[PDB]
Image (cartoon, rainbow, N blue to C red; front, side):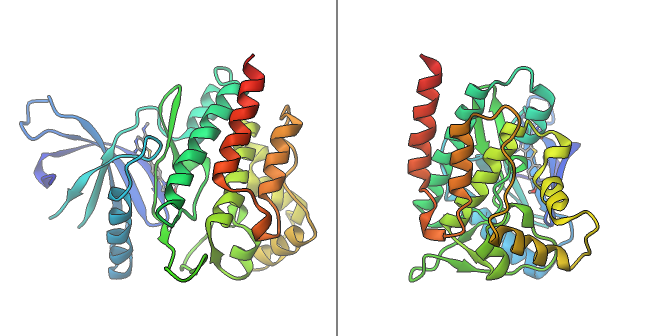
Length: 286
Ligand SMILES: CNC(=O)c1cnc(N)c2cc(-c3ccc(N4CCOCC4)cc3)sc12
């Protein structure tokens, strides 16, 4: 395992749900020849959150895929999850800062990699529940990886869905209708979120074009607080949806809209999404 005393703090990487990820140098020979790693810990350790974190850690190390962040180990005294450090950071920050370097062909390359990572999750009956570009990490210009699994759950053997309502704030603008109304999470709800991720990528993370900003504008910024979810539910019920991003090809927007089907069973599979995206990639190449 990783020893506490040999882990040197370098900087804070992010804060989500109930954790924090820090950039650290694991230097066991204290001879600055050690590798930099990412360390995740609960920002406020609760026994309920500790049990969830333990599960999260088991989920991540049971995963080995090119498009999933690598598990490196754990650190015991306050439990800490040690993961590989991806130098380019989250896709959301990377894309926002590098839009001039990233074209549509590369956006589809990332899209394809995200789908393959998700199809791999589904093969283990894992439901991510938090897909968004901020949870995708960039290893290099050509490779992205799903980098966080804090809300990931395992489907029960007898059901094709999982019910769960956690205390606090949820990323409601990335949530499928049945996740908002019934707290139901499934591969199909991950697909709905994947559609939002696709939307995100093609907006190049323009601040005014974010899902929260767009939906709040459609719902009315003169909205309340507890009623926000209620109005979001109604908007989606009446087929209100995120607009086609500026410059987005019509065939890409259709993938988005198909993922945003109110009918859970009509949403495409991740396997099919990969095939349609790779087909469009090839048609844009030659
Ligand atoms: C430039 N290098 C990096 O920044 C970097 C490198 N390697 C990594 N493995 C990670 C992981 C990161 C991270 C940051 C925020 C969250 N959140 C916020 C969203 O909600 C989930 C919790 C999770 C993971 S950053 C990062």
